[PDB]
Image: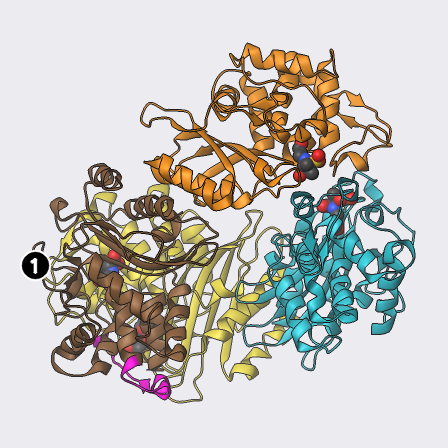
Chain colours: A brown, B orange, C yellow, D cyan
Amino acid sequence: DLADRFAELERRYDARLGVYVPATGTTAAIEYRADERFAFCSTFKAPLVAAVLHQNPLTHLDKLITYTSDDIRSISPVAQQHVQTGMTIGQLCDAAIRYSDGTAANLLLADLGGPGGGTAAFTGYLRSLGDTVSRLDAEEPELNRDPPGDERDTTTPHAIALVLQQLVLGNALPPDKRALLTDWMARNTTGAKRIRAGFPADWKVIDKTGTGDYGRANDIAVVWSPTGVPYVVAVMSDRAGGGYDAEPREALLAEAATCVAGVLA
Amino acid sequence: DLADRFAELERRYDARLGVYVPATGTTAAIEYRADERFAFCSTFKAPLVAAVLHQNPLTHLDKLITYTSDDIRSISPVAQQHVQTGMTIGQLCDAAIRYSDGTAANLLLADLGGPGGGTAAFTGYLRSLGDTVSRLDAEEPELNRDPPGDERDTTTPHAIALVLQQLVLGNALPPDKRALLTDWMARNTTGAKRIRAGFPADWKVIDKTGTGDYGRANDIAVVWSPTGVPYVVAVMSDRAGGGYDAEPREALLAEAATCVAGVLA
Amino acid sequence: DLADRFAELERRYDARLGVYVPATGTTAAIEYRADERFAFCSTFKAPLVAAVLHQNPLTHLDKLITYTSDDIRSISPVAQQHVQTGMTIGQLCDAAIRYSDGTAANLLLADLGGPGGGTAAFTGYLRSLGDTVSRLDAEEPELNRDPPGDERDTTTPHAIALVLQQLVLGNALPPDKRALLTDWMARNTTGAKRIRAGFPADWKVIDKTGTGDYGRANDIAVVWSPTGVPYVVAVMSDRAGGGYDAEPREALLAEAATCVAGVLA
Amino acid sequence: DLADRFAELERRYDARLGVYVPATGTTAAIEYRADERFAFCSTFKAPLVAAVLHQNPLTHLDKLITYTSDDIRSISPVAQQHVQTGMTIGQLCDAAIRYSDGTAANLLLADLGGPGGGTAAFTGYLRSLGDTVSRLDAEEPELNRDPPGDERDTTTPHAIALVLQQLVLGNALPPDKRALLTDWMARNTTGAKRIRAGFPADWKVIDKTGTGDYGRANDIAVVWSPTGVPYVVAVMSDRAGGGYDAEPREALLAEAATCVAGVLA
Ligand SMILES: *C(=O)/C=C/N[C@@H](C(=O)O)C(C)(C)S(=O)O
Ligand SMILES: *C(=O)/C=C/N[C@@H](C(=O)O)C(C)(C)S(=O)O
Ligand SMILES: *C(=O)/C=C/N[C@@H](C(=O)O)C(C)(C)S(=O)O
Ligand SMILES: *C(=O)/C=C/N[C@@H](C(=O)O)C(C)(C)S(=O)O
């Protein structure tokens, strides 16, 4: 009967809440709008880094990439400060995950190559991981402002949680590459008020946030209980009824994570 | 059903969980063995300090009390450093709440005066708050050693929660005296791994812990939601099956408070 | 003295360092190459929006400005996503201060009006604050790429400090317009590795950075001691011996700010 | 001329200040009352843990130590909650450093073995490292209330900084034991408003604090530059002119640390 509390949070925040938690040997899966489509936003930056790491040897992280002023089309708090110096693949992976750097994600997508600047190649990496519903059709910041009902650049809480499970807890990556992604998400600096704020301090939380227009605000995370049991939590939400200028509500994601924590205790 | 999760941690930690959260205008009351009798242990020092504040004026806190080395009976991290100087009533209140000092509580009990070192006077104060169930018959450290089934020095999560609601949230004390009591519990240094560990960091938590033999571990608390809504959480537990030297499981209290936080979210 | 440490980092980083801390009532004035001219770079946007605040009332902030793709010339993380909808006056101020948007600054210069994109109007506001030395002649991205020795688009560490002192601590703007200017500089997102990284955490730091070619890296800041004492710190630097594409060294600005924080404590 | 700022801090805070920083290869040695005697306070718990580490193998840290209520003679936030279950030697080393547990330090002194609870063995360990000035004669908390002028339980900022240098940067311990002591001092929870508050955030600071009567406030630490250069900072202070109940001033230690940070920059 956890769907009642989730439905009450939707009424309180005027939002559509989507929550999925994969099942464990001891607990059942938590599902609220798990198979509904929400916008990817910056949450695609976590499997994108894994895609770059998967198709390249570890030595590729030192390849320097140079870009111009016209490449910075969205908020890039790190790419903005290295236009003259350039950036390696590893620095692009660090900025895309920890600071949600918009330009870093577009260069990482271009590093994947192929049509669409790497969007079709990234979606192919999800299909190889069993993901059958997610899709990425544009770059930043276009993928954030898709109209409601448009299935472009959307995923499901059920789909993105399984992808995050194989990248961190599964064997989709070797231990050396998987340890790089886990450390990057563990030091994320944009999710202090989302899933991290809903879980107690003794719980470990690595995450990658995502914000867009129409009040969109998601956060995919892997949590560790104080005893050490790992759970994957996928929380996504939008407020498309409020319009394009709808303000996201980070408290809804923090409140939903507090509901999930009581069930996982 | 929260009672099912409240019935698993008993089997998981081999304990007897007692939870009570007084109902508010928006939320219902959380009950699990709420009317079952649990030992006061060191939690009685919260209504004990409020008793001294109730009968005595503000200037009574500056009254010095002397004591010899014979009066130090239980754990007294502060009393073992003022045997030559003595402590004023205010210091004994600060030591009894924040550090759970055993000798300070015995001195505050004798400060109430009466039969048995101020125990009957203490129970008499509990009766004025409408609590006719709880009782205190012994002094430190004998009240922690009462065998199970015995009703001496016992209380219930139902009756101690309403008492804390009257003292901290109600009008049991005038505002200037109530501000002093809340500050001491807000700076408690013995409850980091109990209710404070089970609630998210953005929740304010004041508490007074209680430990004892037979695996007794209690924590009565008044928590505040990130929006400012106040609740009262009373969690008590023991493991009488493990014998006299049963080990108290602090993780059971912290894990129980997370369940309460989920429903209260 | 401080001048010898200020003469060491220049050798450590192969740069030309310029510091100025205007004297307050308590301590003296820290000066090192204070009157030597350094490039304005993106630091001119701090007094720019203050000029737009001064000669227009508060209702002018709501004025909409429509622009095309050809107007995007320098880096513009915020201005590049509002080509169809346009931006307001206040939105251009927030983007030019917090994100150092080049397009927003070139539009703010045009909003002040006048000849040559209104650069003389900008300097037409500096002498009114007493600044005789500083000058601005070009728009982005041309003011950043002036050759060394040229005096166009230059100020001095002595010249832009007292203006920042007048604009944050003096009486240059009314309180209604002062609150907005200070808030925008406190939420700056382009200078976490400069003066902010040099001062301890308990020091409030508002700033507006500036970076350009020839290894030019500036940061003007108003810091507050843990006790509430305000100070104006202006650190400008270039590397005019390494070519047009010399790498700017942010570490020198953070080390110089630490060398300023020592005497101020 | 850095001794001029240390004197003004002595004048402003009404306290005697002791500061020593051992000279590295690039910088010189910073001294201010470095050879004067200051009380040990809780700073002796850093070499005490290293003493137990040095005299015993790694698996000795798993030995369970049991104690009674009488062993809690000072503030012991960790030992007070483990009277029933007991504490291992590894847990005693953690609590003595991170939480400055009083009972844990006394038990570790007994683990060293020797006359008067093992204080003669701890002093002998300091003589082994080359320290011929420091001395420990009392236990907790008697070593904190010594009168001014007494050499009992005192060291010097010059001697304690050289002891801490070999224990962390030197090779007084093998890398396995040395990594445990460094990790414990890195996660200290009692020095937030002392040396840590005086250094920029991008400097890594491990430390152990000390506080006692007569306004005594010490903090020994090892800091790391943003580039990775290590320095040892020993800051001690008292206010013995203010009497037994003289309040300590943590801001004096934080302000003196900011002066050292600017010189080491
Ligand atoms: C994730 O990829 C984020 C984009 N950032 C959003 C934000 O809330 O800052 C936008 C859509 C507003 S942006 O293009 O900066
Ligand atoms: C508060 O009054 C005390 C509970 N005392 C326990 C403790 O953990 O300190 C005992 C059982 C150890 S005690 O009889 O002091
Ligand atoms: C102020 O806003 C500065 C722009 N300066 C440079 C920068 O790194 O941001 C450039 C390279 C964009 S300048 O191109 O002419
Ligand atoms: C280590 O230096 C401290 C022991 N405790 C002191 C403190 O300030 O925490 C005292 C002075 C309170 S004590 O004598 O326990």
The residue that mark 1 highlights is A150
Give how far across and how far down residue C213 sits, in percent.
35, 81
The residue sitting at 88% across, 48% down in the picture is D148
- The span shown in magenta is A54-71
Give residue D26's quadrant in the image: bottom right
Q: Is mark 1 within 8 Å of ligand 1?
A: no
| Res D16 visible | no
Give the residue displayed 23% in from the left and 42% down from the top: A3
> Observer-nearest residue: D102 or D72?
D72
> Residue B136 sits in which quadrant?
top right
Q: Please tell me how crowded label 1 is: few (under 14), some (14-19), or many (20+) other residues with Cα within 10 Å.
A: few
Asked whether C250 falls inside the magenta stretch, the response is no
The three-letter amino acid code for the residue at tag 1 is Asp
Write down the quadrant of residue A192 in the picture. bottom left
**Residue A200 % position (x, y):** 44, 48
Q: Between A150 and C169, which is closer to the camera in this rendering?
A: A150
Viewer-nearest residue: C259 or C196: C196
| Image quarter (top left, top right, bottom left or bottom right) of the N terminus of chain A | top left
